[PDB]
Amino acid sequence: PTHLSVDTKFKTEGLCVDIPGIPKDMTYRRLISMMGFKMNYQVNGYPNMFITREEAIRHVRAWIGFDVEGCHGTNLPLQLGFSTGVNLVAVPTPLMYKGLPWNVVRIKIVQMLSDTLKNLSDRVVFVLWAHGFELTSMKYFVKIGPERTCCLCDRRATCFSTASDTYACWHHSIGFDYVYNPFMIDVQQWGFTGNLQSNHDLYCQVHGNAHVASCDAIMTRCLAVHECFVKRVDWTIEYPIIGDELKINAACRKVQHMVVKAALLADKFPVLHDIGNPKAIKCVPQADVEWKFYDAQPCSDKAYKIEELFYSYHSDKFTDGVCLFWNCNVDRYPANSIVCRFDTRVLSNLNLPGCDGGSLYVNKHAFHTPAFDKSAFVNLKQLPFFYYSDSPCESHGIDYVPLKSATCITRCNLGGAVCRHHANEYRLYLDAYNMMISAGFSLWVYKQFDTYNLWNTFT
Ligand SMILES: CNS(=O)(=O)CC1CCCCC1
Ligand SMILES: CNS(=O)(=O)CC1CCCCC1
Ligand SMILES: [Zn+2]
Ligand SMILES: [Zn+2]
Ligand SMILES: [Zn+2]
Image 1 (cartoon, rainbow, N blue to C red):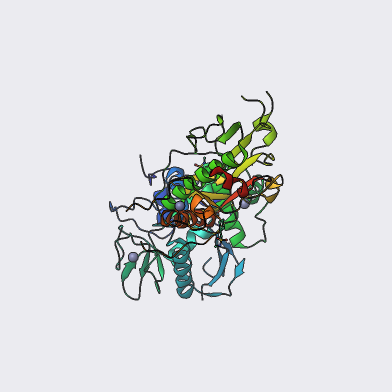
Image 2: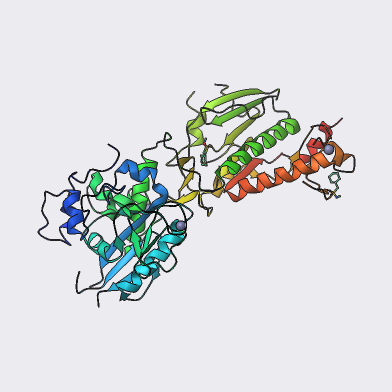
């Protein structure tokens, strides 16, 4: 069992206000037929338009919430809303577009999905809170058939053009008018009491209800992210590489080693309390310090309360030495800390919008991360950029312009002229550091941290 059987039952109660008289006994096979689509007994990679909760989770990057509200259904205008904030009015003749016929609305849908999804996913998963009008509108902008490849590349086809009779992926679909082989999931099938707003509002105060289709589309997708990534967490699911994942992760390890090594050299803490990932390894293995670990998985709902991580009776004395919180998100860091905190507000192909101000950071695994809160850092200050090295000044083995920088903390710089080796390493470090920052990571440190204390570690 990998795909959703078309013979699975579909609960129709949520559809009966838009579709009165709808049979209670209903399968996906009959529903797809009712929606105006014919599967023709085809074994060509597309067994069902609808997918399981598990298939949806693996394809979370493709999720686009979708809602259709009857503006006035054959004779009435429809308002199509998407979790991108777009509202389109389709006449059968928070962005709000005036009423237009389906032939032009479909081009806008294809353009919007393609620009939203080309750098995220090989597909689209329409996330529904199905009431009827959204399912019956699909025939006006969706075409289905065998799984196909793009006409200009090797990627799977996501769009079709009636002008050229050709197929394209999200990257080569300019001027295309049909969404081809989309996927969908009805959140109402999961078992809920009450309407969308009542279930959504139980976990989120950031998305309101301005009474438009896009608001419902946003709440639907938010509710789905809550159920799949906030209340339930699965770190066994791998996600494909779509960007700078490897460079970002490598940069994070480089910066962590640099910062902790320098804090230990500058302030000589006798003990380090490493709080976070239960699979953490000493980031400065050659350091003298008593290294003590404390297990905490990444918090996916609210930030950890420091009182619960530290109290209720370990070294016991977290006030001794320094505390290292490398992506261990707490409500208020103690004054003696070294912190890396992901900024959920960051715009990137890895960072998806999440629940209640949180974001869904997807890099190898999916991590729902609680909203970035500037007040968590009141006892600390921003960590300034610096490169420190005690390695020998020796080239070994790319061209050169002499490096002049006050933040290159090396013997050669102290001696008045940065060596080629330390200039190369400084520039590589600066690139890694800028990569980490741009990815959304933020660095904080105890207020007494001063890189002037590193110069005397060269005697
Ligand atoms: C120990 N967690 S991790 O470093 O694997 C991923 C983090 C990514 C950014 C948000 C917190 C979790
Ligand atoms: C050339 N300008 S500079 O500010 O980079 C001089 C360095 C001398 C050694 C300490 C760091 C600063
Ligand atoms: Zn293509
Ligand atoms: Zn929400
Ligand atoms: Zn040097």
